[PDB]
Image (cartoon, rainbow, N blue to C red):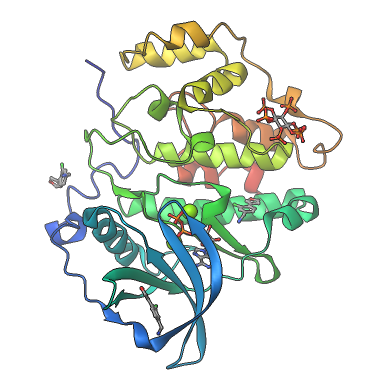
Length: 325
Ligand SMILES: O=P(O)(O)O[C@H]1[C@H](OP(=O)(O)O)[C@@H](OP(=O)(O)O)[C@H](OP(=O)(O)O)[C@@H](OP(=O)(O)O)[C@H]1OP(=O)(O)O
Ligand SMILES: Nc1ncnc2c1ncn2[C@@H]1O[C@H](COP(=O)(O)OP(=O)(O)O)[C@@H](O)[C@H]1O
Ligand SMILES: NCc1ccc(-c2ccoc2)c(Cl)c1
Ligand SMILES: NCc1ccc(-c2ccoc2)c(Cl)c1
Ligand SMILES: NCc1ccc(-c2ccoc2)c(Cl)c1
Ligand SMILES: [Mg+2]
Ligand SMILES: [Mg+2]
């Protein structure tokens, strides 16, 4: 069997807390009334919801209404309890209300509105300083939720709302988030393909908060190198091969051996042999103004196969890459 693993930080935060904090199945959800909200327009969609801009008619304030689609009721209770636990945390989206549609029996979550700036319009305008600034804001949200015993497990650009004009950043979409319990074996079918950590791809179930630090590394690589996504897998198996084409196959076997992971033998047919690439090889004329020795050193410390070797969110905040913020 595989070697057990635990987070290096905030390991026993849920162990020392009462049942009410982490037992989301037992949590009493009090559903408000939808009549306080008038829907304005569709803002987005996801594999799990339909998201609308709305107005709260009791204070003329804009809100966001996330109407939840057919899914396990256990999953909705989990998302509600985590949002309630993290409510008020730095750069965490604020859950304002929970309402139901009497007729169709459909639950909806009501959030604070974020005036999200478009990514395609943002990319070219983003400077080295702006990347450092926003990366730091995400770290504040991750250090906070990890300190609260929660793993986000779906860190990606689509789940980060930025109101560039107000330099306001919010980490959203807590639908895949989970309570960290040391030694727990989690479902590896989480995160979005390009952002999945090697632990998920090799089916190592005892992962932790460090999964979020890998995803953050993928976002940083994509921003500084202007290559979106950075690891462009066409499926979950190919995703590991794309990582192996950068980090090399030697360190992948060291990781598998350290945790006694039973690697699916089909991988030995597609992985091949790949040398470890230097991060400097991703520097080109279009991205050199965003790359620096500090940026490459910070990225190298997040994008590691070994989930225990990655920087924690607090260690990342102390990195020289952030001295200017
Ligand atoms: O980053 P770009 O210069 O835009 O090039 C990428 C990249 O190709 P290179 O890595 O060879 O530059 C992708 O290839 P992979 O990294 O995925 O192997 C490819 O994606 P597909 O292979 O899925 O086509 C993508 O094409 P697309 O824009 O259709 O995603 C293509 O972009 P360009 O064609 O714009 O260069
Ligand atoms: N608070 C928000 N402010 C503005 N837009 C948001 C907000 N929350 C969600 N959105 C939009 O709705 C989309 C879907 O968000 P989300 O429902 O949380 O994820 P999913 O359905 O994929 O689990 C986002 O990608 C974004 O475009
Ligand atoms: N079903 C997941 C789960 C929930 C709670 C705990 C717990 C917390 C404190 O003592 C045991 C553990 Cl270890 C696992
Ligand atoms: N007052 C109009 C209206 C109508 C329906 C909804 C709804 C929320 C969740 O499901 C439906 C909401 Cl939020 C508002
Ligand atoms: N909502 C799309 C989007 C766009 C840009 C970033 C970014 C930029 C620099 O650091 C993070 C992020 Cl996190 C998300
Ligand atoms: Mg989403
Ligand atoms: Mg959300």
